[PDB]
Image: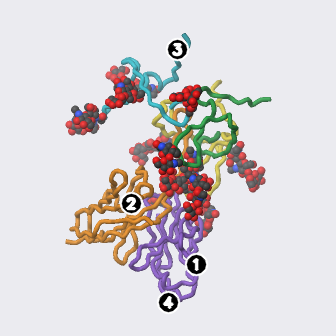
Chain colours: A green, B yellow, C cyan, D orange, E purple
Amino acid sequence: TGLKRDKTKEYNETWYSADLVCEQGNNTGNESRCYMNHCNTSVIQESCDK
Amino acid sequence: TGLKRDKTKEYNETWYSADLVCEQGNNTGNESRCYMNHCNTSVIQESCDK
Amino acid sequence: TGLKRDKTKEYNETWYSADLVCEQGNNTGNESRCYMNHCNTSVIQESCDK
Amino acid sequence: QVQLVQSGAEVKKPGSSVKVSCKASGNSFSNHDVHWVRQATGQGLEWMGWMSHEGDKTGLAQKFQGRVTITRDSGASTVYMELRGLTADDTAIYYCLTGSKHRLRDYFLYNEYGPNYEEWGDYLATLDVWGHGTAVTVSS
Amino acid sequence: VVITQSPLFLPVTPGEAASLSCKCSHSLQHSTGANYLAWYLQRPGQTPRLLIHLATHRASGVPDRFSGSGSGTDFTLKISRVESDDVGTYYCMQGLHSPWTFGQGTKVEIK
Ligand SMILES: *[C@@H]1O[C@H](CO)[C@@H](O[C@@H]2O[C@H](CO)[C@@H](O[C@@H]3O[C@H](CO[C@H]4O[C@H](CO[C@H]5O[C@H](CO)[C@@H](O)[C@H](O)[C@@H]5O)[C@@H](O)[C@H](O[C@H]5O[C@H](CO)[C@@H](O)[C@H](O)[C@@H]5O)[C@@H]4O)[C@@H](O)[C@H](O[C@H]4O[C@H](CO)[C@@H](O)[C@H](O)[C@@H]4O[C@H]4O[C@H](CO)[C@@H](O)[C@H](O)[C@@H]4O)[C@@H]3O)[C@H](O)[C@H]2NC(C)=O)[C@H](O)[C@H]1NC(C)=O
Ligand SMILES: *[C@@H]1O[C@H](CO)[C@@H](O[C@@H]2O[C@H](CO)[C@@H](O[C@@H]3O[C@H](CO)[C@@H](O)[C@H](O[C@H]4O[C@H](CO)[C@@H](O)[C@H](O)[C@@H]4O)[C@@H]3O)[C@H](O)[C@H]2NC(C)=O)[C@H](O)[C@H]1NC(C)=O
Ligand SMILES: *[C@@H]1O[C@H](CO)[C@@H](O[C@@H]2O[C@H](CO)[C@@H](O[C@@H]3O[C@H](CO)[C@@H](O)[C@H](O[C@H]4O[C@H](CO)[C@@H](O)[C@H](O)[C@@H]4O)[C@@H]3O)[C@H](O)[C@H]2NC(C)=O)[C@H](O)[C@H]1NC(C)=O
Ligand SMILES: *[C@@H]1O[C@H](CO)[C@@H](O[C@@H]2O[C@H](CO)[C@@H](O[C@@H]3O[C@H](CO)[C@@H](O)[C@H](O[C@H]4O[C@H](CO)[C@@H](O)[C@H](O)[C@@H]4O)[C@@H]3O)[C@H](O)[C@H]2NC(C)=O)[C@H](O)[C@H]1NC(C)=O
Ligand SMILES: *[C@@H]1O[C@H](CO)[C@@H](O[C@@H]2O[C@H](CO)[C@@H](O[C@@H]3O[C@H](CO)[C@@H](O)[C@H](O)[C@@H]3O)[C@H](O)[C@H]2NC(C)=O)[C@H](O)[C@H]1NC(C)=O
Ligand SMILES: *[C@@H]1O[C@H](CO)[C@@H](O[C@@H]2O[C@H](CO)[C@@H](O[C@@H]3O[C@H](CO)[C@@H](O)[C@H](O)[C@@H]3O)[C@H](O)[C@H]2NC(C)=O)[C@H](O)[C@H]1NC(C)=O
Ligand SMILES: *[C@@H]1O[C@H](CO)[C@@H](O[C@@H]2O[C@H](CO)[C@@H](O[C@@H]3O[C@H](CO)[C@@H](O)[C@H](O)[C@@H]3O)[C@H](O)[C@H]2NC(C)=O)[C@H](O)[C@H]1NC(C)=O
Ligand SMILES: *[C@@H]1O[C@H](CO)[C@@H](O[C@@H]2O[C@H](CO)[C@@H](O)[C@H](O)[C@H]2NC(C)=O)[C@H](O)[C@H]1NC(C)=O
Ligand SMILES: *[C@@H]1O[C@H](CO)[C@@H](O[C@@H]2O[C@H](CO)[C@@H](O)[C@H](O)[C@H]2NC(C)=O)[C@H](O)[C@H]1NC(C)=O
Ligand SMILES: *[C@@H]1O[C@H](CO)[C@@H](O[C@@H]2O[C@H](CO)[C@@H](O)[C@H](O)[C@H]2NC(C)=O)[C@H](O)[C@H]1NC(C)=O
Ligand SMILES: *[C@@H]1O[C@H](CO)[C@@H](O[C@@H]2O[C@H](CO)[C@@H](O)[C@H](O)[C@H]2NC(C)=O)[C@H](O)[C@H]1NC(C)=O
Ligand SMILES: *[C@@H]1O[C@H](CO)[C@@H](O[C@@H]2O[C@H](CO)[C@@H](O)[C@H](O)[C@H]2NC(C)=O)[C@H](O)[C@H]1NC(C)=O
């Protein structure tokens, strides 16, 4: 959900292989729950610069 | 919702006509729902000073 | 809820007598609703350095 | 092609209560919603209530508000619908039927502290399998 | 919230087309764009059979002659080449707000 804190907007982003850690499980669904690499250790800030 | 992060409390606050942009729809309800004028472009800070 | 903003994690913290205010009422449940002593007036910080 | 089995017809005095029992082959109720419909001879169909297959949102109709109670056995093996305050107008054939729902989000307040505030509402779309029905006669 | 079904009584000559109307106007405060409406046919001595769901999609096994159309408040059900098998009462089921209700129904016979 964006700046307007009332509604959400689903997007898509494509990571790479070495940028995700996935939770293994017996889930048969075609969707694989999977977090980011290091978002449970410390908040990571972008490099929104040149 | 207040500082105590629970048990929200309804308020009122009346604006002027030059401070709202309201979506137009076919809704018949007596309540017109809409947002601020520039709250979907950047956060606006109060001027809590003299 | 913790840093992974998708799930909850219950803890227990054992406070002291002089650091809690509890709601008074006709409730019969064995659980007593209480808040921190001074979190409805300001945000409190931790004496985080040594 | 799920099969629904309902209890036999009953005859009751005015002002008493009836408790119907409904079952689905293969415990289909554990994955599909449950509903209840009635109709009087020569009259239109009348809706009664429902209950989510997850068992979260349970309610009744405005007409029978407080007059009916819907309950199921653990595991959704059986579903029981109980009605009280019977009268002559209550004489109807009571039907047990399955279905599903479209649980969508109706509100959202991104709570920066703690979890997010979500509100969900259930809207009835699917009505696939109908039960044979139970005939109830309110008479002395 | 009420439902108006017209006409009450619709004699149809065999091989002719038929039109049924189920109108709802109390869509207070909205929620989902596609208001849920479901059409069912109850033949004598038979359980009601689903015909249309979401007001535009045919149900499984329904012949193409049964078509449901409409959006917003006014909806219509169109039947082509009516036959004896189509004799019965057509019910339109609101699927918007809790509690939900049946439609008063429209009676169709062979003229
Ligand atoms: C982030 O936001 C998005 C957007 O809000 C969230 O997506 C929502 O996610 C929930 C699940 O978390 C989905 O719920 C599922 O919805 C279907 C029905 O939805 C179908 O119809 C919708 C209506 O379409 C008509 O109306 C619209 C206008 O309103 C018109 O434009 C259309 O033309 C139609 O006329 C339609 O909007 C839906 O499209 C969306 O979903 C489909 C997939 O369904 C996507 O392809 C689309 O791109 C789009 O996202 C859709 O076509 C229900 O059928 C599901 O019900 C099942 O699950 C329930 C519990 O979740 C359960 O209570 C039901 O009984 C049912 O059970 C299911 O599972 C059982 C086994 O467990 C089965 O036995 C059973 O058969 C069934 O399979 C479900 O409710 C929302 O549709 C989806 N979108 C919206 C708008 O709500 C997203 O979830 C958010 N993020 C998170 C983390 O939540
Ligand atoms: C953030 O989330 C990630 C993902 O859940 C999490 O990673 C976890 O780290 C711990 C600590 O290292 C792993 O602990 C495992 O414990 C089992 C117990 O039997 C071990 O067998 C595992 O060994 C693996 O790794 C060895 C190499 O060190 C291999 O030789 C061996 O074959 C095993 O592959 C392992 O030590 C845990 O497995 C991961 N998670 C997953 C899904 O693997 C991380 O700790 C989290 N960080 C936080 C919360 O700060
Ligand atoms: C924050 O939210 C507001 C409110 O939704 C939003 O304002 C919107 O801006 C867009 C971009 O300009 C407007 O887009 C419209 O697109 C239609 C397409 O046909 C045009 O016809 C519209 O023209 C109007 O304006 C002209 C003058 O420029 C008039 O001459 C003309 O007659 C029309 O009135 C218009 O360009 C959109 O209409 C508005 N929405 C509203 C409700 O006004 C704003 O962009 C958002 N800011 C963000 C997301 O940063
Ligand atoms: C944060 O939460 C706390 C706890 O709820 C809250 O404390 C409240 O402060 C007000 C401010 O005075 C108290 O107001 C009461 O009002 C009644 C009205 O009749 C009085 O009778 C009360 O008197 C008590 O205190 C006297 C001493 O001042 C005693 O002599 C007397 O016997 C009574 O015990 C009292 O003035 C209110 O009572 C408390 N809360 C509770 C539960 O008592 C504080 O205000 C909150 N801060 C915020 C919202 O900023
Ligand atoms: C994961 O993806 C696969 C591949 O898309 C999905 O399998 C396909 O699922 C669809 C939807 O259920 C099936 O369509 C239906 O199949 C039945 C027969 O089972 C048929 O009678 C219907 O008319 C309709 O076509 C499709 O057949 C099926 N295909 C295969 C090869 O399996 C699967 O469902 C997805 N699973 C999840 C959890 O998303
Ligand atoms: C928004 O501002 C309005 C003021 O215009 C506040 O309205 C006031 O609300 C109180 C109760 O919350 C009203 O008192 C009650 O009035 C009814 C009227 O029938 C009476 O029956 C009750 O016994 C009680 O006295 C008060 O009249 C009303 N004043 C108005 C409308 O002028 C409202 O509280 C504000 N919203 C908030 C604080 O959330
Ligand atoms: C709050 O702190 C207490 C410690 O005083 C934690 O209590 C402990 O909780 C664990 C399970 O979370 C208990 O283990 C289980 O005990 C039951 C007792 O019958 C046993 O049958 C199970 O096989 C299992 O061993 C443990 O006994 C218990 N210890 C106590 C009460 O002294 C509690 O977990 C903390 N709350 C949290 C973490 O939310
Ligand atoms: C662990 O995961 C595997 C693979 O997902 C599971 O294997 C399934 O086992 C059930 C019966 O227990 C079968 O019906 C499925 O066809 C098997 N495959 C899948 C993809 O589900 C296994 O059961 C899981 N073990 C658990 C949950 O304890
Ligand atoms: C937008 O809202 C207006 C006002 O409610 C709608 O106006 C009605 O439109 C229908 C056709 O869909 C007419 O039959 C009615 O006579 C119109 N007036 C009223 C008072 O209902 C308009 O239809 C809406 N736009 C849509 C639905 O696309
Ligand atoms: C909008 O306001 C009007 C006027 O107060 C409401 O109309 C009244 O509604 C009440 C409640 O149903 C009735 O008892 C009155 O007879 C109505 N009077 C008139 C003149 O219409 C209307 O219901 C309100 N609508 C909404 C959506 O709030
Ligand atoms: C506040 O809580 C007390 C304790 O539960 C209630 O005490 C009861 O009050 C009722 C009358 O309202 C008496 O009949 C009971 O004998 C009292 N004791 C118990 C154990 O129930 C008190 O009523 C509550 N205040 C209210 C409801 O206003
Ligand atoms: C508060 O704690 C007491 C004591 O543990 C609970 O009383 C017991 O409740 C269980 C569960 O119903 C019964 O099986 C016991 O027989 C009860 N014992 C006594 C001495 O009362 C009580 O239920 C708890 N109440 C709440 C609201 O948690």
Q: Is the residue at mark 4 from the same chain as the one at mark 2?
A: no
Separation (CA) of disc 2 from disc 3:
57 Å
Kind of residue at disc 3: Ser
Say which chain tag 2 marks. Answer: D
Q: Which residue is mark 2?
A: D49
Question: Where residue A6 sits in the image (x, y, percent)?
Answer: 59, 43
Q: Are marks 1 and 3 in contact (CB under 8 Å)?
A: no
Q: Position of residue D11 (x, y in %)?
A: 23, 70
The residue singled out by tag 3 in the image is: C47
Same-subunit check for callouts 3 and 4? no
N-terminal-most mark, 4 or 1 = 1
Secondary structure state at the residue bearing disc 4: loop
Q: Determine which residue is flagged by label 4.
A: E111
The residue at 34%/68% (across/down) is D94
Which residue is the site of mark 1?
E65
Label 3 resides on the chain identified as C
Q: Residue at x 36, y 78 (%)?
A: D42
SS at mark 1 in the image: loop
Badge 2: residue crowd in 10 Å (few <14, some 14–19, many ≥20)? many
Tell me, yes or no, whether dots 1 and 3 are on the same chain. Answer: no
**Ligand 7 is located in which of the four quadrants?**
top left
For the point 50% across and 62% down, the residue is: D125
What residue type is disc 2 on? Gly
SS type, badge 3: loop
| Circle 4 Cα neighbour tier, 10 Å, few/some/many (<14 / 14–19 / ≥20) | few
Between the residue at mark 1 and the residue at mark 3, the CA separation in whole angstroms equals 77 Å
| Quadrant of the rendered image containing residue D37 | bottom left
